[PDB]
Structure formats: C-alpha cells, structure tokens
Length: 9
Image 1: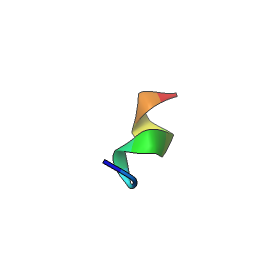
Image 2 (image 1 turned 120 degrees about the horizontal axis):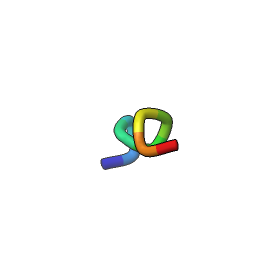
Image 3 (image 1 turned 45 degrees about the vertical axis):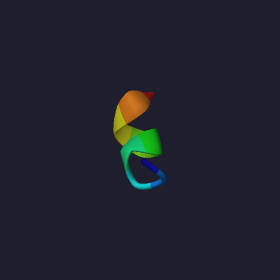
C-alpha cells in the first residue's frame, strides 16, 4: 500500500 508506507514506518 502506497498510503500504508507512512504507517509502515
């Protein structure tokens, strides 16, 4: 998920 990238970090 491109938007989940921020949440991933």
